[PDB]
Amino acid sequence: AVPATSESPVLDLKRSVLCRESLRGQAAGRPLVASVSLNVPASVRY
Amino acid sequence: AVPATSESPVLDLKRSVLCRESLRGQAAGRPLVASVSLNVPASVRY
Amino acid sequence: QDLEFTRLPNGLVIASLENYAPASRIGLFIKAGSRYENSNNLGTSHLLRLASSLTTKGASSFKITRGIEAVGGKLSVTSTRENMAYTVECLRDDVDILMEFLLNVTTAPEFRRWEVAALQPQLRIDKAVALQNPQAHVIENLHAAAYRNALANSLYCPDYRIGKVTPVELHDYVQNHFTSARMALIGLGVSHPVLKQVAEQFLNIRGGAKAKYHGGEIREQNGDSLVHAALVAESAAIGSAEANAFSVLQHVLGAGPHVKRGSNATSSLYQAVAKGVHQPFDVSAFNASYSDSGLFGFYTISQAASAGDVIKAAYNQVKTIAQGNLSNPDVQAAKNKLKAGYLMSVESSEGFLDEVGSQALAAGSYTPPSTVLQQIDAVADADVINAAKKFVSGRKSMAASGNLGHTPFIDEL
Amino acid sequence: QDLEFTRLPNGLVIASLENYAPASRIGLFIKAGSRYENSNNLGTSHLLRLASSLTTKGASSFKITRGIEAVGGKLSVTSTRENMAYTVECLRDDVDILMEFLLNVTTAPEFRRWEVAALQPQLRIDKAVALQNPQAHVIENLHAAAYRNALANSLYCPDYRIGKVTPVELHDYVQNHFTSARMALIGLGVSHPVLKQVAEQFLNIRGGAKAKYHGGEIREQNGDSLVHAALVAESAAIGSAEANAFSVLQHVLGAGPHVKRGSNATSSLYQAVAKGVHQPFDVSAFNASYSDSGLFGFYTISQAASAGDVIKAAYNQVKTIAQGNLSNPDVQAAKNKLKAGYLMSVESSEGFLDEVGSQALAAGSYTPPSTVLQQIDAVADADVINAAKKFVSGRKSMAASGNLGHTPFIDEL
Amino acid sequence: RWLEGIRKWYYNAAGFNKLGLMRDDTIHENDDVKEAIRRLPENLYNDRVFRIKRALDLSMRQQILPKEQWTKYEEDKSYLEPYLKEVIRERKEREEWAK
């Protein structure tokens, strides 16, 4: 029912990172999970 | 001046092999060489 | 209100907490993850994940979309390496409508030639999107490097197979993996007796190798100014007591952030790396744990030139933990993190359903949160040092993506 | 008529046989192969190979094409891992017209922003074509697996760099590598004194790490019914006497076919493999030899299911040669092949020019064919057994492409 | 030299400077000019694009810029010359070769 945390486009240039404070959280700590849906945008997890 | 042993197309399905007698010669025995030209079609070597 | 549990003679697990909430989540968990592909049908489970809402026997492709949307509902399919999870949400009055759709999707999909072929390009769209995350590159490569067969499989269909996953393959995969012996039907806001009866009448479907660790390395050269990199050794199987030790070691070293824009003063790895190199970076302990095997290590994100320094600094930190430099206040803090992390992960009724189903497949029954916390406490300081020692002397697997000019090899470390 | 030779004080080699043929081949050989790229400018030499006939200072892009074609001539650019070779052919009366073009192309290319950018898609066309040969996949991977840096470089530009090789990079590559100290100007059907004078006046241009063997494996999973695979160990540097031993060992084992549609009765590998498995296959000894290093092994082409059996059978054959099962009649036959092969390779005035130039870069001067044959004879039976022993105990590098379900890993062998 | 008085006069009379145009913006686009434009670097091209956009917008309103904002005669760089000169020089070579 509810739209996801991020709208996904293919062929769209990606968002930059220029500091420590925005780069932390990103280092993967657990194995991948993959969800696809009817209502919610597809997204992969650590 | 002279055209090469093989005319090269991109997006063209490749020629099959179904026997020993046509498959011999193919196993690479020396390192790659690459030629490009003005007159002769580009081709790579063993 | 507390959870109810049933395992039928045919192997199938039913677990359900009737909590009288207005919303009802139902999940059918199946041992049908990417690991159960072989080299002939690679990426089949990826297409199968995209393929719910294709025509079934009792409902059309159109009816699945319209009928579910009509009642404001959701149908999701979630894959790990080991499991596939088909989940439906709605307002409580429409549970048996969504259930009918869920059963159709999982027990009798038709996989029509024209529909299956029409879906092929979706593999490229879905993959392309997912591979925008550089974590996806590295973790998928890491596994491919670390294993010979089952867990080496990627969750996303290899390029060469896109457009080539057949209807037969989809049928075969369902027929061989979607079985009572491999299934757990989990639920919230629905009575246990009615779930049991559905599972007996509609989910009684008859039945249909071990992961070899290898140790390798895969290197994606791509010219980013940042280098993502992961270095792991073989860990311990989930369910074993040793696995708990690695989970504690993960939180000793540092397993992701607690404060917004924070400098991570308690993270052992982050401080170890930040001592030597001050430019933008991130480092975390990595801990995967599976039925057959596990991977433990760390993941770096560093500047291209500094990748050598960051990885070596991080690796050195694990070595001193393995050598014995580890006090109770660290192991206590690490436990507090993990204990809090677990209870927080089952805080939402989404994550709770995931843990109930997840446990039900990998183990016999439900372990309550209180028993899990007691098992975390059961990890002694000595067990943490052993996990670290295991990592240091273990055969290594590595993966990287970036401009790797200054990223070392395994045998350079 | 016999060859003349000059090495100028600035480092540059001139070698030329005036043979009074109607056609004249001139080649400018430069130490500027793929090995001299680093991780920042990967695929630059590939673009540079495509980039002759772009505008120069003394001649337009248009004039290079029209002027050369006007006299029925040819201009080719040929790259190995270690050298680049710029070659011109024509009827003898037009040599100094082609020479003017060759000098322009090599000594003063303009690499105009709009021209260089227009050429970018040609990298994809050229690569795409070349990678139609599965030998190209495997050999390029094999090197990438076997080395840490120089020789690990592919001759074809990596995907991520296509569209991104800059004019600066092309200028830098030429300025840093196309120098008197790194150049040999070779020729047929032209006088030596006039070549020397051209080299003094137009090729006097001022000057501008070692290959670390690694041992790795790269596996292209792609679902072909045939599996191409190569397994090599570190060999010996070209110029060293040991290299000659490997060349003889190559021909003992079997280095490609002599009879059309023939069953290769003298090929040690082919018979070793054909004993166990009768379905379509091909096997050959692989021998690369470079300035810093070398790779020796074998290449298999087998059915997907039989890849394990074929590789192991081939590997076993080298082991028995290393153990000492090798008679004079074998080593004599192998020498006869190599001796004949060498003289046949310099039989054409194309291949002769290539050997004159090739030698001139990797070594000081020209070794005559008669001296080369004497050096082949100098290889004793014991030297062949040592080369084989070196291969067996050497750290391995492997590469494969195909449906690799039954292709073993290095550590499975 | 001596006609520099008239060149400076004509410049202001012509009056493209009042729209914040340089001379090479006012060149009529034939096949050579098209190619010359096509060869301009990102900076020089986007300036051209804006200067014209600005001029067209001013023309639309039937207004001019403030006098301070007018292109000074001395500051009018001949930005298109090196590209256009070579485009022409090239074509004349092909036209020669064709005979």
Image (cartoon, coloured by chain):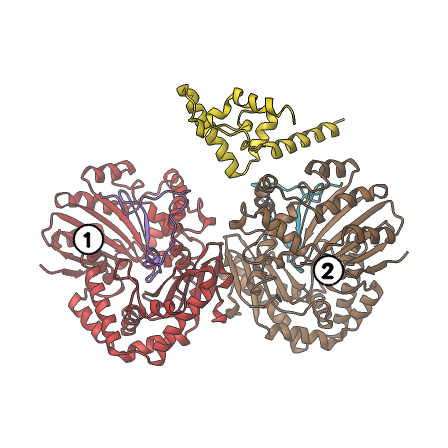
Chain colours: A purple, B cyan, C red, D brown, E yellow
**C105 relative to C372, above or below:** above
Q: Which residue is mark 1?
A: C199
- Disc 1: which chain? C
Amino acid type for the residue under numbered disc 1 = Ala
Q: Which residue is mark 2?
A: D181
**D207 relative to D387, above or below:** above
Q: Residue at x 17, y 54 (%)?
A: C187
Q: Is residue E33 visible?
A: yes
Write down the quadrant of residue A33 in the picture: bottom left
Q: In screen coordinates, is D104 left or right of C307?
A: right
Observer-nearest of E1 and E42: E1
- Where is residue C397? Give x, y as percent: 43, 67
Element assignment for label 2: helix
Assign the N terminus of chain D to one quadrant of the image. Answer: bottom right
Observer-nearest of D145 and D268: D145
Observer-nearest of D191 and C411: D191
Q: In screen coordinates, is A5 left or right of D1?
A: left
